[PDB]
Length: 545
Ligand SMILES: CC(C)[C@@H]1CNC(=O)c2cc(-c3ccnc(NC(=O)C4CC4)c3)nn21
Ligand code: NA
Ligand code: NA
Ligand code: NA
Image 1 (cartoon, rainbow, N blue to C red):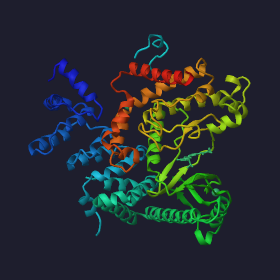
Image 2 (cartoon, rainbow, N blue to C red; image 1 turned 90 degrees about the horizontal axis):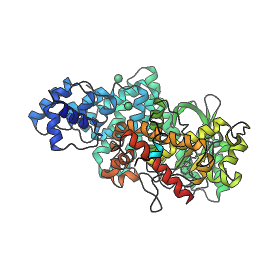
Image 3 (spheres, rainbow, N blue to C red; image 1 turned 30 degrees about the horizontal axis):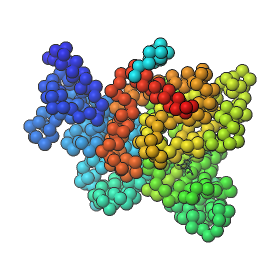
Image 4 (cartoon, rainbow, N blue to C red; image 1 turned 45 degrees about the vertical axis):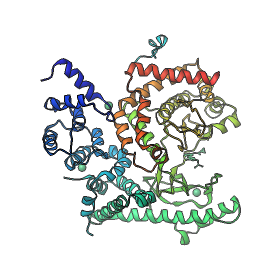
């Protein structure tokens, strides 16, 4: 029905990011050719955005069109679960489309889906109970029935990994005392989700009932570890005495039940089943907050070191590591493995939680003990035939992880980057830790948008090396890949705006735009490549000037 000119304009509208507000003219255009648009699954979110849900005649027709639309993709369904959708039929449609995801993808979204329960009908949850262009770089830069609660519990009953995270994510929401004080009905809702969850597990078959007892075992274990950390952190004396107390309490299994337990899924990574904590290798970090390093004995004879923080809110780190995990999985789906280190983070309360400990050396220590990253690589991965006398595999891994983290920390606006938050493995993996400053916040004024340093660049042989050329190519390639998933990434951030995460809570209404602006969606792919190269070029020039 539309001509080539309106079809061109409709294509622009359907192309918009999920964040873009349609003008009155665009809404009218979308609504007029709604029947024409039923063929385009990507047009459905735009159409639903044109509906005045508070006008009954309009809602009725929008729901008829909803039933006739080419079904929308999983990633678009996340937009229908935000606070901007109340219509029960729309929200059920979202779950029906979300349900086509496999559990691997669902797990990538689950932190946000647990936030989205805030936007569901709280009575239904309760009732279920039983109560620009650089010419010289053109040629060198070629282009490459159920509601949400019922649904999540249903999938969790069938998948112990999903059940693990659903349990702990909900526990943390229940313990959020800001939510308790300021939004008591939301606190009640999360309690009811947990009661619904427990009730469903108790009704299941033999292994589903065992899942309930394993979550209880984990909760009890974590409670004991918290009791231990309180005892250690209040112990009289100095650090020697505190470490001795830490190890003595861990060694007293009859008292504390932390060093010799029947196999329990590790909350941090429930695929890993643990036999207890090794008493003799546990110590406190020197940090004044006294987190502990703890080595878990695993089912298969391994050791899994963690950081257990007590007295500290891990939720911002948890979100950032969950998003880095997602970005890594999206890049890998595009067959780009940049050797990233999305270490696990799991809050077990609003004031304690786990991080996966990655063996590595802080770059500041690399420099102080070996003088440079290349000297470090030459010491631990020598290769006579390799670049600068370093193993080609290690250098490749370094260039790739450098590019991946440059692009990812740029998108996430990570600040407070110093050489003790940058870690390096002897296999060449560079990675970032400690995400207390995100979305453009920095402890110093005028943080640069791009977080590079001379040491990284010298590590890849300087700006004229082959490795540096490959670094730049990996940067703009990862950038183009992540732009292609900007709808999904932005939809997930939109679900976090009411989370009590410090750097989001500061300006919830501006949070998603802080991320969107970094993708430069106003730029074509070709323009975006030159933008990213100007970013790197300007950053590196400043380092050496
Ligand atoms: C005092 C800490 C809690 C420190 C500060 N805040 C953090 O959030 C954090 C994350 C990590 C971390 C995560 C994964 N792996 C490592 N690995 C290493 O530290 C090896 C170099 C020795 C560190 N550390 N921190
Ligand atoms: Na299903
Ligand atoms: Na230990
Ligand atoms: Na895609």
